[PDB]
Length: 256
Image (spheres, helix red, strand yellow):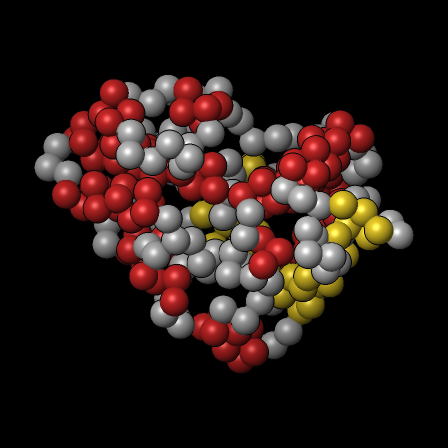
């Protein structure tokens, strides 16, 4: 399984990769892990963690480099080389340094502050809703809310019934949710339903983030076309690299 905060990328507030990157950093997992759990949980970082298919701690192979050549904006340099690791905080949920990198990222993206509220380049305030289904999600979402408030972002936390929750998943009627994807044994055809651009605009698909990049589709095609161990590992690893660089998810944690 993979679990995370999912940015509904269809909505204007989350169109920009630096913004999703900033909000991802703003979330303090270690506060949550120590304060709501007994550190019984482990942070999920990428998309194929603890598998030969993970890209996390290794530099891109030549085949990967060849797979990605056509797509220069897809992967971050730190992610291309295996340096990248998900950001952690130092305990108490008021980290100045963490918040500082995100603030930096938002300025680049055109964000400013008015009367203590973060504001988009279009003057609209950065305010959005997080839809949860369970009390445990609500707690986690409420902790995120506190992190976001510290930079003038207002996250409204909702917990609703299942009919509504499932209706709204199906319609993509949400700013952000907690989504989980039960990974198959090896990535196969289900990848198209999760990440392909076509599945962005088909209600009831599992492209919760509305991700839609030619690079993503290309990697998926490469995974499915692979006839060797080496080509398949490079295709999945390259995909991980793009999805990490996309910040389509703010990854949460696995039972481990």
